């Protein structure tokens, strides 16, 4: 049964609610992004209208085989009427195709559902600037002050400089980057650009990338592993055993691996600066954990919410424990007393 924080009151709508069977009263199912916890339940047998971005609708049709007649892609930054209700899709600064959804209820209430997002000051000049929001359905993944991490730009600078130094010292080093979902494509694309290489990957991953409307993508990726010195592998294989095994397969072209695991936050964030990050090493294999986040830090979250000034907040993440819920409610009240709304 569908939880309350996935239902939009005063409408026939749900958000990211595909694993509950037929939801009673739902006339349109919205999907914020193509991450498995959110699309869980969709398949070629789904027969209700799905509303989403163009990129998400490319992934539904090619990866999950949802039939075309049930996919309703909407342009971003554009007022659209869905089953009698005005909606707008906004870029969420998450993975490719990820959106926030603004719902203009027939009674005058305005609701923002962030989906998963990385808040940014650029959102203060979107179509959100133009009107009041009553209710905020908020991605609270990192809603505690211990969650700090650098900008995406600082993290990519570290990765490019690290990779370029290693391969210029040793032209026979291979770079490997872990993946298990869409998102974080800048990590492997930026490294391959500095090295003058395409990114090599499996046919299944190439297929997924080809759905993403990334400009000039045919110039940047390939399935021919032998022609590439940046390889993508499943995240599970980014360990000493999995990397040793991969280096065997390359036929003595390479004699060293430098590997990257983009994680979210890890507790080594509470002590170490990005500049000071060091790898784990075993013989000719080195593994870097790099804190590349596609969710808001605590400070970015707090800035967005204090700017928006919602009347009510509904968290969508960390809702399963009383301790989490009480922590989050305490910070919401702090923010509201400090800013004065
Ligand atoms: Ni996500």
Image (cartoon, rainbow, N blue to C red):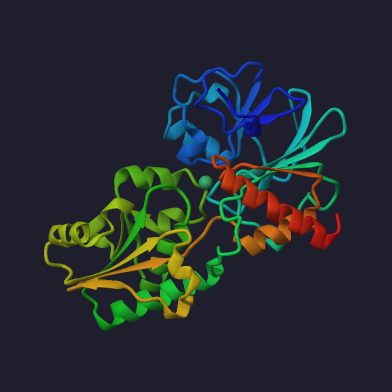
Q: Residue at x 52, y 73 (%)?
A: 154
Q: Position of residue 190 (x, y in %)?
A: 44, 67
Q: Position of residue 60 (x, y in %)?
A: 49, 33
Q: Is residue 317 visible?
A: no
Q: Is residue 34 left or right of residue 260?
A: right
- From the viewer's perspective, is residue 141 above or below residue 227? above
Q: Residue furthest bottom?
A: 169
Q: Residue at x 43, y 34 (%)?
A: 62
Q: Residue at x 72, y 61 (%)?
A: 303
Q: Position of residue 314 (x, y in %)?
A: 69, 41
For the N terminus, which image quadrant? top right
Toward which corner of the image does residue 339 lie, by quadrant? bottom right
- From the viewer's perspective, is residue 64 above or below residue 224? above
Count the numbered circles shown: 0
Name the foreground residue: 101 vs 326: 326
Name the foreground residue: 145 vs 50: 145
Name the foreground residue: 142 vs 109: 142
Q: Is residue 227 left or right of residue 181?
A: left
For the C terminus, which image quadrant? bottom right
Q: Is residue 62 visible?
A: yes
Name the foreground residue: 165 vs 278: 278
Toward which corner of the image does residue 158 lie, by quadrant? bottom left
């Amino acid at each position: 049964t569908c939880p309350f924080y996935k239902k939009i009151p005063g409408t026939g709508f749900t958000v990211d609610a595909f694993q509950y069977g037929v939801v009673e009263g739902c006339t349109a199912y919205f999907l914020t992004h193509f991450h498995s916890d959110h699309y869980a339940g969709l398949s070629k047998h789904f027969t209700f209208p799905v509303y989403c971005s163009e990129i998400t609708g490319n992934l539904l049709k090619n990866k999950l085989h949802v039939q075309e007649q049930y996919i309703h892609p909407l342009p971003l930054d554009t007022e659209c009427i869905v089953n009698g209700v005005k909606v707008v899709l906004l870029d969420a600064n998450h993975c490719p195709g990820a959106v926030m959804i603004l719902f203009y209820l027939p009674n005058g209430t305005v609701i923002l559902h962030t989906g998963d997002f990385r808040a940014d000051p650029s959102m203060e000049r979107s179509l959100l600037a133009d009107q009041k929001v009553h209710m905020l359905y908020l991605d609270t993944t990192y809603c505690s002050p211990e969650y700090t991490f650098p900008s995406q730009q600082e993290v990519i600078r570290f990765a490019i400089n690290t990779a370029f130094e290693a391969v210029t010292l040793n032209p026979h080093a291979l770079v490997v980057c872990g993946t298990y979902s869409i998102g974080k494509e800048k990590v492997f694309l930026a490294i391959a650009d500095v090295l003058g290489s395409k990114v090599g990957m499996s046919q299944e991953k190439y297929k997924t990338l080809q759905c993403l409307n990334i400009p000039e993508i045919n110039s940047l990726i390939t399935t021919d592993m032998c022609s590439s010195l940046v390889h993508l592998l499943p995240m599970m294989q980014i360990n000493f055993k999995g990397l040793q095994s991969h280096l065997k397969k390359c036929g003595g072209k390479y004699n060293q691996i430098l590997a990257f695991r983009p994680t979210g936050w890890t507790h080594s964030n509470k002590f170490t600066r990005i500049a000071d990050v060091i790898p784990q090493t075993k013989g000719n294999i080195s593994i870097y954990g790099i804190p590349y986040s596609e969710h808001s830090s605590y400070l970015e979250m707090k800035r967005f919410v204090q700017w928006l000034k919602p009347q009510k907040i509904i968290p969508t993440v960390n809702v399963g424990t009383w301790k989490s819920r009480s922590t989050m409610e305490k910070y919401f009240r702090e923010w509201k007393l400090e800013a004065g709304y």
